[PDB]
Image (cartoon, rainbow over the protein chains, first blue to last red):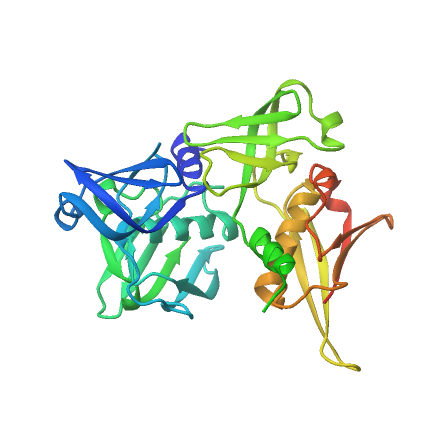
Length: 185
Length: 192
């Protein structure tokens, strides 16, 4: 067992906090949120620096993972449409190699509740699901990966042997445009 | 359209859990603290577990964590759920247990689901069994979409010993630290 794996387990097997439909105040590369008398400071470390305006920004959601709550990225536009049913249903396929020629495949529905969702959030919640249901980080992850494919055929890959890169945590996608999620373990 | 009572059970048993493996816990008073760089977890000892866990450091523990109270605290505050870790950290099926779920669909009809329920821990807390079983029922059998009424889980051991989880209320806090030998679970029967 590597320390690197133990660290990934520790980082990912933890609570997150959701802030919904709040204003964020940006100065420099930090955005601050106040909620129930607690301050959450969020660092802008990628393309989110171009999206979030200096000063007050209204009607934001934030997916928070403590690195006060201090966190990186995870900011999105709040839902503009209030949905009863899910925003998008996405088929999640997890293929676990069980031998030279054998694979165990689990094919389920993964529910998206946000019109705009950060890579941070998708990454964190999918790894939490794999930790809970697929023994992720009980063994060395090697070349295991999550691929999120979009309806236009574009895709994003999360390599499971390292944390999501900080520069990607502020990256956002349209939840309605997610086509499939495939995981190789 | 569900009672407040049922809404609360649904909210509780839909919370995430954190199954933490092979770590040290330091007992001071009736609280065991587990600490890593990313996360502190404070566990209350509220029953038989007070006699099982030693003051000071306790090595090689598993802890099945469910956060109690406001969703907002940095630390995890949880009750019970501490067990001795497996002899090795290799993944092995400790026991295969028949899970029989019988749901009344009318005066004279029942739908019965029979599946294998895997146990991977040599020592498992009632917290863990209760929580993961209810989540399974929530996900697969619509638990707490309707009033649970008299619904129960009965867990029977190889020697005939038994535990019941009454589904119309949370598992009692005093039982959360109770532990059983996973290899000796014989069957689980759920009436819905």
